[PDB]
Image: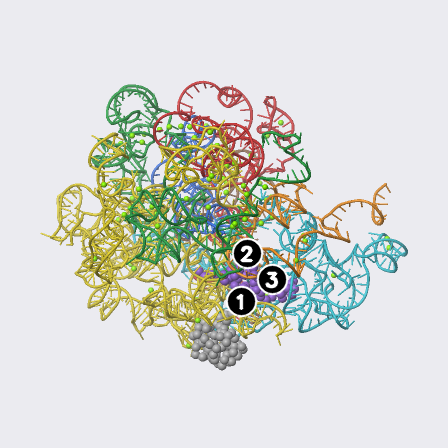
Chain colours: B purple, C yellow, D blue, E orange, F green, G brown, H red, I cyan
RNA sequence: GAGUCGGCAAACAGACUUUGAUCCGGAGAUCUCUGAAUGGGGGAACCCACCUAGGAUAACCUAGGUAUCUUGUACUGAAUCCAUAGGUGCAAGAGGCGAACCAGGGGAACUGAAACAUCUAAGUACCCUGAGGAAAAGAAAUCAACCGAGAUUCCCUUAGUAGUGGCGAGCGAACGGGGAUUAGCCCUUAAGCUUCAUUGAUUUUAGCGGAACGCUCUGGAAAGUGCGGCCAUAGUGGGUGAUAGCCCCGUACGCGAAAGGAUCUUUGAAGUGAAAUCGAGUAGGACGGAGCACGAGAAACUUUGUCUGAACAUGGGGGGACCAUCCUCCAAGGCUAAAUACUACUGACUGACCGAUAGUGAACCAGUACCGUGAGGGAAAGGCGAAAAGAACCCCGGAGAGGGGAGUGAAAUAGAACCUGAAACCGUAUGCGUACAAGCAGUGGGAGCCUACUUGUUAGGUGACUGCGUACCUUUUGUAUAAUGGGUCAGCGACUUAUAUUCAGUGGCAAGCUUAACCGUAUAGGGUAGGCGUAGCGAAAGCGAGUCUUAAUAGGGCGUUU
RNA sequence: ACCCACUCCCGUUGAAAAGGUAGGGGAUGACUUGUGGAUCGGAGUGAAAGGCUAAUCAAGCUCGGAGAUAGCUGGUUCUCC
RNA sequence: CCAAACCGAUGCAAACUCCGAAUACCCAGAAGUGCCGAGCAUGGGAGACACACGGCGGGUGCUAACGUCCGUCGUGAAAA
RNA sequence: GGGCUCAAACCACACACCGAAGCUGCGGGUGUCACGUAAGUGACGCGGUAGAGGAGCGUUCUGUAAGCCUGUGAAGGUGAGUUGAGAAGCUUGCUGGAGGUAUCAGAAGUGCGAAUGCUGACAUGAGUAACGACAAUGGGUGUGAAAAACACCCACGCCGAAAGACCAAGGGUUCCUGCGCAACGUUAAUCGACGCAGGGUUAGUCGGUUCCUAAGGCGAGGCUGAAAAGCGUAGUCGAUG
RNA sequence: UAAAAACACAGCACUCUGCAAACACGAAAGUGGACGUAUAGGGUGUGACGCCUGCCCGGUGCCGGAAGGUUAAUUGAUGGG
RNA sequence: UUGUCGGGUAAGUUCCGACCUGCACGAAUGGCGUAACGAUGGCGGCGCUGUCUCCACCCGAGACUCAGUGAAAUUGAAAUCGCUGUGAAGAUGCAGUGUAUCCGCGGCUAGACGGAAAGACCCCGUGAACCUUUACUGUAGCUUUGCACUGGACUUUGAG
RNA sequence: AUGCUUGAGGUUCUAACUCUGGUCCGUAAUCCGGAUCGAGGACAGUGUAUGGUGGGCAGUUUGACUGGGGCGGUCUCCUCCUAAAGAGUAACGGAGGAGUACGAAGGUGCGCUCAGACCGGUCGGAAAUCGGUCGCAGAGUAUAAAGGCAAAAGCGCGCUUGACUGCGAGACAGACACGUCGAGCAGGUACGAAAGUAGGUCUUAGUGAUCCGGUGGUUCUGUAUGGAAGGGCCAUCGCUC
């Protein structure tokens, strides 16, 4: 970062933003990853057993990335409009 | 030991897919004399210039 | 179980030993003086005593006792009547040393911040205290987050993240997860720990046995050559006159303790833990500090120098200002193994460690010589040979030094300053050149001479005469420079290593890839906690192949077609 | 005598890390001197020169922090394309 | 006796211009030649940021300096 | 520079020649492209500091290797020859006397002329300066391998409020005798404060010890201080008295 | 490498100090001052002796005063959350 | 500024006396005098002289030679001349030219930018040290008040 | 006001506390401690908190450029020349300016054209206002210079707030950070009948990053939960840094 004594770029520019502490427990699961879960039910603990999310993850969201291979039930897991359509197209369903 | 990121650089340069974002200078405290166009075009983030990437990439411990 | 009287380092003496010596191990005895040093003193290794008991008559001798302080106890005991302070005796204990590890008291600066004061270095160095083989800590007035976990300690992650920071340089978590270990007990008195018995197991401190090879060649010597065998739960050990599974000592393996030490145990005994009886000058508060990653910050929590100061489970603490609700715990009393740290010391084993300028400073009589008043600093120095067979004798010489023969030896130009024996540097001999000739000393041309055979289209040595030609390094715009550095030789002497990381090359696997600690008859295999990738945009909530900005689905930013 | 150190010369790889020869000053005093003792490192001591504190002084020596730091100087070792 | 203006003749100017080149620069199209490439982009690794002289155009100095400061080209640097 | 003048000067013109590592010729090596799925051909290149890129040599150790070489001679040392573009390799004579290592890999304390580098050895200066008070020597005799220096004798000279004799401190055997001379002695040495061995120091009265205290030290308790300690009472040491 | 005109000095003056003195060394205890007591002790300047030592109190220091202004910790009225 | 005048000398930037135009004396950082004193500064004189004109002779000790012993700094290597040029700008080494047989010894110091000490002057380094102050920030000590140790009583002092 | 909570000065008292005052004892003793007498006395003194003072002591800072350094000057921005007819281009080269101003001196619609000279005319004059001719920008343009200016960009008047909010194709300039110009789209306006014009001023100076703090908004976050604090985002303020 030393620029010869000129005001460095890492001090000419302003600090901005804040880090989100609420986003440290969240993870995103692709639709291509839902078929790698065991037991036909996609859940918080079942995604941890499949090693698709970390152990500390407490809330999961599914977004459309890849194709849902097999019909699975999403229990307590949020999804996007595109992901929800793809999951239900393959025969899946959602539970609160 | 493991490399220590410069705290000040990490507070001014966010890494996104596409470069490092940063705010603009000259938007802090002398703003009446500045035109609205100048203040509006100095608002928002921006990608790091090509010549500053390696230097900042080294300030952060990403290289 | 046959030699021995330690080594440098032998020579003669005098002896000991199969009536079992030397030697090795256990247990005893003796154990001067100094040193905590302790009867008093002192310039350490010295000086001077006293008390008791015994025995000598002379001018002493033997044995024991005689420090201080702490704890306990007994007797005495002031000012002052009782007391107390004090004094005397006794018993027990302590003191000192030791490399590190542990807990605690005190606590820098250089340095970094490209200056410097906050900050950093760093609670480091150092000084001091105490303890133990470990120490400390330790059984939630703890986290968590409405689900739960369940003491302490240590390792890997989370993560160089949250945060902190003249928001500079820097500092830097926790939650959660994976592991190693696992243990909890009491104040209506226990788990433990210590000591002394005691019952058995090992273990340690000397040792014993331990297989199997000959001929031949070279050679000083065979273990090496050639041929043919044998042992192996013993084959890459050390020696032996060169390279040995079978020559010796060993090795695998199997045995072994009169005696002592130690560790596990089975009971028993006291002792302790033990603070008694659930915690008040305590929790909380104000001021000033310190610590918590957190530098006053919006600053919770811990701690306390000053000052204050509750409640009593219908109560109290915490959940990071603070309030309410909820959850969770019960402080002001204690004890507690394992996993963890270290190695001055003892043994074994090992090394893509050194091999005498290396490796310890020290291979050698080295913390020595030497230097210093002192604290302290601090070297140099290894090799004959297989075996002293270490040169009888003769000669020169000063009854020298040193040599010449002789002899020993495989070898003496291996002769004791001894393996090899380089270079600088110094000589002797031979060949050629050199006393009318100017300078980086060479290089190009080149006569003659000398030597040797190949006898002149050769090899070697020298080189008259002549063209050209001002070393090298460094540093510089530029150096013959009269700028720098080097007297020469030999040896040594400078881009390393660890941990994070990026790019490239080359491999493995591939929408997956890879494990860390750790476990593991251990480079295998397991362990997938974690890290990276498969999605981005946004400060963020969030949305998501989109997202952000915006009134805008418009424009534009970044992203998406691998 | 003893203490001192004003001048010149010598000496300057010295006989000597401060001397010698010749001259010079004090020489009963605020004198010189032996033995023993006290004071020392931001400290001492100083009839005061920043003098002296073991040939070392505008902050001794010794070990440690310590391989301080050095934007400076020097040096940096085989070959070829 | 001095002198505004005007008229005519007559000169100068880096900070005057009624004018005004050569070159140089920008763009387009086109042949051949590029040593197999010149160009550009991205990334790995630098070194360098004391320059010197000569020519030409200048400032400065005295159109002095092997002076000093720019522009531009050549050589030295790093080239026998 | 010699020298030069109808030039060996100057002006003009012309034809020759000399002249470089430039160009050409001949032979060789190498880089990059292209053609070649080849050996190789073709074209153009090949000065170079800082610096980037590429390709190698060699050294020590580990594996390959319980292999291979080696007393019919290893490593090392010293000559000769030879091979390669180079770092270097190979063969051999002599010396040496027991170890070495092919190949291909792997690791590095891996390459030295410079650092007023470090250690040792040895040069140059140079057989030069100097041989340390200018108090001073001469001769004879002896001994001895050897005498200016040792011993003795005869002379001479120097100090004599020391250059003589002591006490203290300090040193520690240097004292004396026999033997001896390598080194030490600024020369030689028979001599010595030097080497080897032996001998030598005798106390009621000398000086210590013992007794007593000065300055000052230490200091039971004690007072003070984060600790370490500081101060100090009773005491106990401490001569220079 | 400086012996002086430098330092000291007798004398002078200013100032502090009532004794558990001022002052100094010491985290402190204590010690020096001093087993002294203003004719004493400390600090400062001047420097035998002789004649003398003038003017300035604005600045700075020191001494004395305290009406007013300002002013610390502390206390916590009041307001706003 | 060697001020000017006077004295002293043949001649006096020094000296002594004086003037006052004191760049920029001055009264206890004392002013002005002052006997005695001083290895104190300046100036003049007598004596005396090798200080000098101008050195000569002599005496010892070195130097020199012989015998014995035996250093030093320095040193890239040397087959190490002059001159004039050239040149990192002052040449034994370059160019041209001149001179010059080889090697010692005693002497002398013109050069070898001779030896010695990584210039001390000067400048630089975001170097050091020590010193100063009304530089900054601190701090020992001294001092102020609150609270504690710390109490009784009586009196001048606001609101309940 | 009998009586009542409690501040601040003074005077007494003794009982804390102090005595480097006497006496006694421990005790063979100037320490010390205890007892007692005496003297002070809630003072002094000490801890803690706080104001002052404080080179007694400490850690440090004390710029650069520069024809050596110092002294003097300069340091950012604008204009001209140097500057070699694109851009750029140095000197302690040659000359000047800036660190503002204006709610009108901005926008628009409408309308106008200066300076100067001469002649005539009360005070009135060289020069005031008036009329006429010439004049043709020699004036003006807030301000220095340069470049511009007739659709005047100069001057007057009416109405106004476009000195708007979101942006923004595309460029210029450029190490970065900054900087400049801007058609067009949307929202909402002003002036004009309308086409249109307007995102400040003829243009080029009039300026200061980050950090930190303050103020106005905010659908963001909110350490168990709901809030809040605090933080983020947007707007804006505080540097002769
Ligand atoms: Mg996982
Ligand atoms: Mg803002
Ligand atoms: Mg004793
Ligand atoms: Mg004793
Ligand atoms: Mg009694
Ligand atoms: Mg102990
Ligand atoms: Mg610094
Ligand atoms: Mg123990
Ligand atoms: Mg324990
Ligand atoms: Mg529960
Ligand atoms: Mg056997
Ligand atoms: Mg052998
Ligand atoms: Mg409790
Ligand atoms: Mg508390
Ligand atoms: Mg609490
Ligand atoms: Mg909370
Ligand atoms: Mg408890
Ligand atoms: Mg060694
Ligand atoms: Mg050797
Ligand atoms: Mg024989
Ligand atoms: Mg041998
Ligand atoms: Mg030998
Ligand atoms: Mg000849
Ligand atoms: Mg010659
Ligand atoms: Mg030839
Ligand atoms: Mg020549
Ligand atoms: Mg130069
Ligand atoms: Mg040259
Ligand atoms: Mg040279
Ligand atoms: Mg020379
Ligand atoms: Mg040299
Ligand atoms: Mg006299
Ligand atoms: Mg001085
Ligand atoms: Mg000294
Ligand atoms: Mg110092
Ligand atoms: Mg350090
Ligand atoms: Mg160093
Ligand atoms: Mg073109
Ligand atoms: Mg520069
Ligand atoms: Mg430059
Ligand atoms: Mg230039
Ligand atoms: Mg020049
Ligand atoms: Mg120049
Ligand atoms: Mg260069
Ligand atoms: Mg020709
Ligand atoms: Mg040729
Ligand atoms: Mg050629
Ligand atoms: Mg060819
Ligand atoms: Mg070429
Ligand atoms: Mg090349
Ligand atoms: Mg070898
Ligand atoms: Mg060498
Ligand atoms: Mg070199
Ligand atoms: Mg000589
Ligand atoms: Mg001579
Ligand atoms: Mg001589
Ligand atoms: Mg003599
Ligand atoms: Mg002899
Ligand atoms: Mg005598
Ligand atoms: Mg004798
Ligand atoms: Mg001799
Ligand atoms: Mg003797
Ligand atoms: Mg004492
Ligand atoms: Mg004691
Ligand atoms: Mg005594
Ligand atoms: Mg005596
Ligand atoms: Mg003197
Ligand atoms: Mg005086
Ligand atoms: Mg006169
Ligand atoms: Mg006079
Ligand atoms: Mg004066
Ligand atoms: Mg006066
Ligand atoms: Mg005076
Ligand atoms: Mg005198
Ligand atoms: Mg001689
Ligand atoms: Mg010359
Ligand atoms: Mg001479
Ligand atoms: Mg010199
Ligand atoms: Mg220098
Ligand atoms: Mg008080
Ligand atoms: Mg200071
Ligand atoms: Mg510092
Ligand atoms: Mg400067
Ligand atoms: Mg131009
Ligand atoms: Mg041009
Ligand atoms: Mg008129
Ligand atoms: Mg008129
Ligand atoms: Mg205008
Ligand atoms: Mg909350
Ligand atoms: Mg906010």
CA–CA distance between discs 3 and 2? 20 Å
Name the residue beneath numbered marker 1: B16
Work out whether disc 2 and disc 1 sit on a shared chain: no
Nearer the observer, disc 1 or disc 3? 1
Residue A28 showing in the rendered view: yes
* Disc marking residue B63: none
Mark 3 lies on residue: B26
Label 3 chain ID: B
Q: In this view, does C197 lie to the left or right of F37?
A: left
The N terminus of chain B lies in quadrant: bottom left
**Which element carries disc 3, helix, strand or loop?**
loop
Q: Residue at x 56, y 59 (%)?
A: B51
Which chain is indicated by disc 2?
A
Marks 2 and 1 in Cβ contact (< 8 Å): no
Structural distance between the alpha carbons of marks 2 and 1: 25 Å
Measured along the vertical axis of the image, is residue C227 above or below residue F14? below
Q: Which of C88 and H14 is in front in this view?
A: H14
Circle 2 or circle 1, nearest the eye: 1
SS for dot 1:
strand
Does residue C113 sit above or below C367 in this rendering? Answer: below
- Give me the disc on residue A3: 2
Q: Residues within 10 Å of mark 2 (few under 14, many from 20)?
A: few
Q: What element carries label 2?
A: loop
Give the mark, 1 or 3, whose residue is nearer the N terminus.
1
Q: How far from the left and from the top, in percent, is residue H147?
A: 47, 62
Q: In which quarter of the image is residue E34?
A: bottom right
Q: Do labels 1 and 3 share a chain?
A: yes
Residue C225 in the image: state x and y as whole percent: 27, 53
Q: Give the residue drawn at x 43%, y 74%.
A: A50
Q: In this view, does C353 lie above or below F240?
A: below
Q: Can I make out residue A59 in this image? A: no
Residue at the spot x=65%, y=65% of the render? B36
């Amino acid at each position: 970062g030393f620029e010869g004594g000129q005001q460095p770029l890492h001090r000419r520019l302003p600090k901005f933003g804040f880090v989100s502490l609420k986003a440290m427990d969240r993870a995103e699961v692709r639709t291509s990853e839902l078929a790698k879960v065991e037991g036909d039910v996609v859940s918080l603990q079942t995604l941890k057993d499949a090693n698709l999310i970390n152990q500390h993850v407490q809330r999961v969201k599914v977004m459309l990335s890849g194709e849902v291979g097999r019909a699975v039930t999403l229990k307590g897991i949020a999804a996007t409009k595109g992901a929800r359509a793809a999951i239900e197209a393959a025969g899946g369903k959602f539970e609160d | 030991p493991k490399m220590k990121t410069k705290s000040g650089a990490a507070k001014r340069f966010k890494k996104t897919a596409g470069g490092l974002k940063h705010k603009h200078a000259f938007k802090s405290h002398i703003l009446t004399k500045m035109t609205t166009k100048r203040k509006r075009q100095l608002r928002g983030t921006s990608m790091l210039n090509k010549s500053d990437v390696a230097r900042v990439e080294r300030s952060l411990r990403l290289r």
